[PDB]
Amino acid sequence: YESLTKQYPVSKTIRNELIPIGKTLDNIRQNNILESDVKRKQNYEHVKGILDEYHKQLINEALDNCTLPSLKIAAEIYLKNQKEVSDREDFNKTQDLLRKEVVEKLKAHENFTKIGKKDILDLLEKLPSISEDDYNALESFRNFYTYFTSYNKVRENLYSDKEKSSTVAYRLINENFPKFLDNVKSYRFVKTAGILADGLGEEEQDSLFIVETFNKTLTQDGIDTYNSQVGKINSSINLYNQKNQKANGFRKIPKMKMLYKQILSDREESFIDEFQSDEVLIDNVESYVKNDLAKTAMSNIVFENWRTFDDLLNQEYDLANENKKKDDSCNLIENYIHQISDDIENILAKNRKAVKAIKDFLDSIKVLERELKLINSSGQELEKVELKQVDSLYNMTRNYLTKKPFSTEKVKLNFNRSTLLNGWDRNKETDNLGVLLLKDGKYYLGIMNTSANKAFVNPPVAKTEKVFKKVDYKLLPVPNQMLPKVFFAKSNIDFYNPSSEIYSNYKKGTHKKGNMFSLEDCHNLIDFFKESISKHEDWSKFGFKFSDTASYNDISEFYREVEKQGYKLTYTDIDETYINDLIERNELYLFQIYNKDFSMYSKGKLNLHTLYFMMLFDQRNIDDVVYKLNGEAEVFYRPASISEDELIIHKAGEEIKNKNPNRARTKETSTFSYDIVKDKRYSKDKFTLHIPITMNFGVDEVKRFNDAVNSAIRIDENVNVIGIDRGERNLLYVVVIDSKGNILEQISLNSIINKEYDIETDYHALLDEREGGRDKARKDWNTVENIRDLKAGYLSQVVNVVAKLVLKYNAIICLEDLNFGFKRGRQKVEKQVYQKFEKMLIDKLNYIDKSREQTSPKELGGALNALQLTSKFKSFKELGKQSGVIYYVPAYLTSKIDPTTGFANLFYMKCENVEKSKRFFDGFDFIRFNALENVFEFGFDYRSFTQRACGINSKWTVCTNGERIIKYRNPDKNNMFDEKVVVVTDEMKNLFEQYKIPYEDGRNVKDMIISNEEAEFYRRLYRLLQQTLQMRNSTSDGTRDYIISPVKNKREAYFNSELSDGSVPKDADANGAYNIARKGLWVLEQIRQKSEGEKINLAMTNAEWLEYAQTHL
RNA sequence: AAUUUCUACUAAUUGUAGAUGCCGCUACCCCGA
DNA sequence: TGGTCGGGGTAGCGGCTAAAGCACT
DNA sequence: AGTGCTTTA
């Protein structure tokens, strides 16, 4: 499995730590960044609600009020069967948004705001603010490096693929017209809204047949006009919705109309305009006739009852009168809350009034909205008026904590250079302000001061032999763009004439995508590029070796060859004393980096991320196709969190005890030094970096899952398979196997152990009893352990275990499916944390690394070339397919039950009627009894059962022997139950003695039982019949294992889990893991059966699975 | 009870063993004061 | 069941982005 | 005769 190595350009962002070195307090202000007092954020009442609010004008004065409304502009049946046979993929385009130029009509108006042109947001005041304590008019701050592609322009594509299901400006026309073709295929006499709308009497629209400018719902008036009034009238009326019949209540949750949820620009942008008095203004100042009704209590300020008159009317018949469920008219029991919305006869009429009296008044109308319940004004009036137009902006007034990660109004400050760190190339040394440097071992970092940026352009040669080595590099970005950018600029055209024919060819674009042309002229263009780069000196410093003239790289291949060669790092000696001589002038912000790892006596193994950063500048290695520093690397300061006083800590003499068993025993004193210990990471200030990384830079191929597995598929080196399962006693018991089902491991991941350190961790009961502690402590207050953080850490540790197993035994991972599977079901892990375990196991299997103090990195797990075992995942919808080396198989009717009979659920369902029970018995061949082993054995054949193709060969004779510890129900003493049957046999000898039947003849005693008729007799016979087959034991507290299949496995084995043999699963969930492994080997055989890049589906049928499980020997 | 970040660690020790894309685009969900 | 406020996550939704003209004071 | 840069490409 030596393929799959650096076969996908993965990328990461190392998050390292900074500490200064030298003086490192350069500036007179002592900030060293000058992001130390922004002051733009405290008392933000002047500025709040300006930019994002005037986005409302920016959208309103640009969108097209009168679009091309006609759905019939396509002029097409679509698909009603009244058309020609030849579709020719045109009808699906008619379903699709085949129009193009409505965006062109949208963008007709540039639409700058009343307050200011873009220049007010682009002119550099070079200040954090201009506003004042009294008021502000055109407040702004400096530009901060390309807001355009990032913050505000994302809102300006509404008919596009923005990947959010609310900007519904074209999915409405995409969906409603197919729905109307359905509504004319069938007719609307099944829906309730056609006539429940006692008035309008329509499902959605005033007249459903006609088209309409549905974007009226998108604007300020919102979906209230579309929905809210008929929502209000929807109540206990229409008793046939509450009294079933052929229609008008065809389902319990119909709600037959909906326009899809409010657009991104809605729930947003309350009312305010450019005025010379400022307000925080979270509330509707224009007009709050809105009422988000929530109709339970009226006059709750001055009534104090959650239901107004229901509280007054009665208190006994609220529960004394029987509920509606068993005793089914809704209009007499629930119509109270529908007639409760008695409308207020009048229209607190108030606006933002008293702010001018003193400088500080904040929230008048917000307090009015808070204290007053919704105004009960904008009702319904039995017909769907523009009532409740301003719920859409009260929806800004509420939930304002939810929507605001980043607009352009709140970007953070940094060094006095917007482009900080955008590129650390040779030529851009002067402007990008960044410089890399390092001594031996300690990795330094330099940032030039703004005053003397050009001071570093002249490094004098070495004088003293105290080096302070400095690193620089050189590259060539985006060669699709730089190559046409250079040699076609008007300046370089003057400095070097190109041929007019080639310029004409490129301007018309003969050589671009989608054309047949003279390949010799394409070669002429390529030569023009090559020789005009030969003209250069800065570009010519690169060792560029492009292709040959016999057949040159295509233009995409040309840019690939340009990009992959274009990166070279080097270094030059610098006098340390000279750095000391210059830093006095406050001209260079120096830094250096370390963490837990960089310390020689700290011999312990490295963190994985300090290995990458350390090996990045491994100057002895070229790092040609290995990690390359790239892109912006913005820094981040945080302040100190917790004080030393709050750090409660013992002084010298802290011989405290160990929490762990087997180390609280051996070393209870906890021998230690007296550098007394505590988490210090929050005890001080901090500086942090982000270094983007393109691990496996320059790799020339992105591939797929079949590509990411088929190399293993031809020649195996992987045949083993990991099983995974969960259960009660073991949380996540795992089982690996071999090709032919030989179990090779039985380790419970409840227990893990540091083998190299070779001291037992006793992880069992540090897992199960600790999560039990969380279970019994989380009910009343938020425990220290989050509800899933311990599971996250445990699964994180398990990733190392499974990765080591994969690399040791060659085994491939075969986690259970959760799509072809049916239920959600009772589970040991509640919210499908197993799903994010799949995600984590993919995410790490993108790349184990040793991460030790010294390395010889030329290895598969040597941190140079990490094996990319699985390609990246896209979606859980994409899951259910083989994610590289993480296959999936279903898990249903086999997670608990061995397949030897498998009828844990009885082959028939439970019997109630006496004659049906008799018929159910009559399929049996013989019910018998032998007093030797006391076995009251039975007999039956497969063919006489429902679903007579599900199983295969149910001719086995279910026996009855051995004890069972089954979970009785004997609720006499408040849900008591007998913990066991004494033995499964002999509990019905008394039942036979009730009739005194000759049960020792060897006859089919059934012949008498059909003649016997007693309800309790057959009820108890049912209980013992289901219980003798209950082959999994309900393990007690202080668990005991008994996997006891009544059918013999040819040797009276019963797969008895009390035994010690390895092939026998030790526990029930271990047997389930074994079953998942046996499905895993089958799906691997299914894959091997194929012989092309095409692969059959991963799924299984229950019949086929039961067939193979029967034929597992 | 030590970190750069998270779980758990004491683990010969101002540390141990294993894991992680930071800013960022706005959305859904699912049950609930 | 449209009835209102969540409430915290879930999943598919920018990244893994760096030189050169060019209009510049 | 020009440094900031938003532009491109």
Image (cartoon, coloured by chain):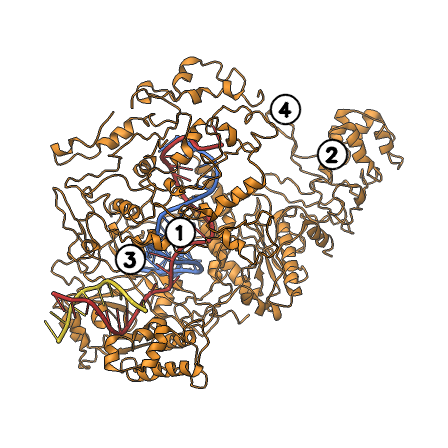
Chain colours: A orange, B blue, C red, D yellow
| Mark 1 vs mark 4, CA separation in Å | 68 Å
Q: Are marks 1 and 2 in contact (CB under 8 Å)?
A: no
Which percent across, then down, holds residue A249?
56, 30
Q: Mark 3 or 2, which is nearer the eye? A: 3
Q: Which chain does tag 1 point to? A: A
Looking at the image, is A181 positioned above or below residue A542?
above
| Mark 2 vs mark 4, CA separation in Å | 20 Å
- Amino acid carrying mark 1 in the image: Tyr
Q: Secondary structure at mark 4?
A: helix
Place residue A565 in its image quadrant: bottom left
* Residue of label 4: A972
Q: First in sequence: mark 1 or mark 4?
A: 1
At horizontal 30% and vertical 53% (from top left) the residue drawn is A152
Q: Are marks 1 and 3 in contact (CB under 8 Å)?
A: no
- Amino acid carrying mark 4 in the image: Asp
Place residue A327 in its image quadrant: top right
Q: Which chain does tag 4 point to? A: A
